[PDB]
Image (cartoon, rainbow, N blue to C red; front, side):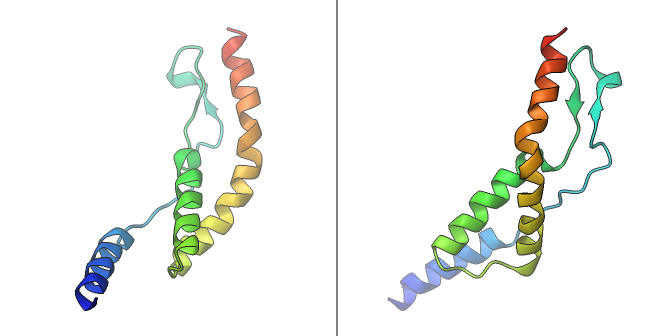
Length: 97
């Protein structure tokens, strides 16, 4: 049993040693870099869902989530709120082409 616990702890540490960042200065469609396909050049593009599933997994499996991840997730939710809909404008701009 002690061995098994050690295995769990080692895998958990190896996985836990990771960080993220969601800040962005290109919040807008960077149109002028591609042709008729606006690029919303943003760090929260996959980071929101990755952090949500990560925090969900850790919580559901009773693992302490570091404060860095918790803060970034509290930001990620507020972001997702509007990111679910920015796709409307980007799709409209790309399809009108």
